[PDB]
Image 1 (cartoon, rainbow over the protein chains, first blue to last red):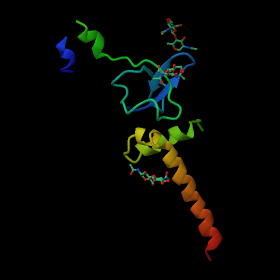
Image 2 (image 1 turned 90 degrees about the horizontal axis):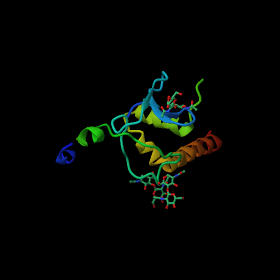
Image 3 (image 1 turned 30 degrees about the horizontal axis):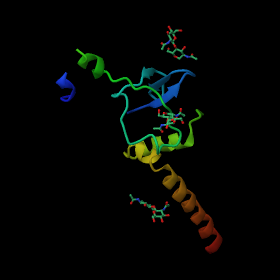
Image 4 (image 1 turned 120 degrees about the vertical axis):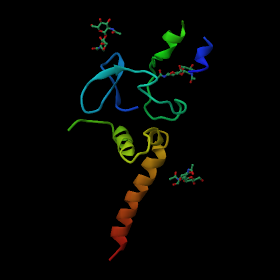
Length: 7
Length: 57
Length: 50
Ligand SMILES: *[C@@H]1O[C@H](CO)[C@@H](O[C@@H]2O[C@H](CO)[C@@H](O)[C@H](O)[C@H]2NC(C)=O)[C@H](O)[C@H]1NC(C)=O
Ligand SMILES: *[C@@H]1O[C@H](CO)[C@@H](O[C@@H]2O[C@H](CO)[C@@H](O)[C@H](O)[C@H]2NC(C)=O)[C@H](O)[C@H]1NC(C)=O
Ligand SMILES: *[C@@H]1O[C@H](CO)[C@@H](O[C@@H]2O[C@H](CO)[C@@H](O)[C@H](O)[C@H]2NC(C)=O)[C@H](O)[C@H]1NC(C)=O
């Protein structure tokens, strides 16, 4: 999830 | 991930194997392994990713 | 009797031994061969033995 929490 | 991929003639679902209860195919209904090049009888269809519309905000 | 494709039946029998079903579909030629060869050894044993 942490790469998508770049959003 | 557990169950079978089936089609009603137009759409693809995953069901448990001992009772017909169809679900939309998603990235948590399923697991990945490798390219489409290897598997005898693979088919092309969408997998919905439930995080993507949430993470769009 | 509910019909099921034989390679998909064998994928469920792989889940029944704790091996993930992609291990069958990614190795299906090698599992279909070697099954066929192991059956050939039954014929050769029963033909040659006494
Ligand atoms: C396969 O299943 C899909 C999903 O249930 C069917 O398509 C839907 O049918 C309902 C009711 O007629 C419509 O309101 C929807 O708009 C349809 N589309 C979707 C994506 O939900 C489809 O008709 C079934 N196919 C067959 C041949 O029975
Ligand atoms: C399943 O999807 C793949 C990728 O979208 C399709 O492969 C392409 O097919 C066209 C027409 O044969 C070729 O021009 C492309 O070069 C192919 N791309 C790749 C990456 O191989 C494939 O044809 C689809 N399968 C079916 C049965 O429709
Ligand atoms: C797993 O074992 C099989 C044999 O049980 C290996 O397949 C053989 O590979 C050699 C390569 O030179 C071929 O000559 C044989 O004909 C193959 N046998 C069959 C039945 O196809 C396979 O390479 C092994 N895989 C790994 C990852 O070790």
